[PDB]
Length: 129
Image (cartoon, rainbow, N blue to C red; front, side):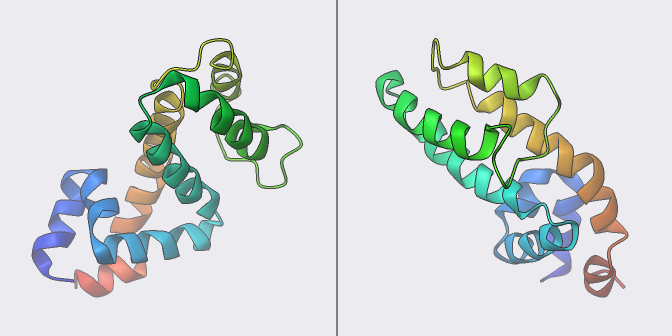
C-alpha cells in the first residue's frame, strides 16, 4: 500500500473500504473483531442500494431481513436496538432508504471503533511506520 492511500484512510471511511488493500485489510480486520457479517451485510446493502424498484426490494428485504435481521438469525449484525425495527417497518413500505439507515450504522460502527483501531492496528502501523 502506498503512503498516499493510508493517509486517505484517515480522511474518510469510504477510502479505506474503497481501496483494494483497504478492503483486504479491512475484511481481515473484521475477522479480528469477528465483524465480517458487517461487510457481507454491506455487500447485500449495495445490491439493495442499486435496485431502485420498490417492488423488488420486498423479496430480498425479507430474505436479508430474515437472514441478517431476524432476532433468531445465527449471525445477527451488530446494530442498535431501534435500527432493526426500522428495517422491519420498511416491510410495510420498502424504500431505497430502508437499508441506508442500517448501512449508516455499519459505517458509524466501524468508523467509531475500526478506524481508531486501524490507526493503532499493527497492519496500519506496519504500513505507517
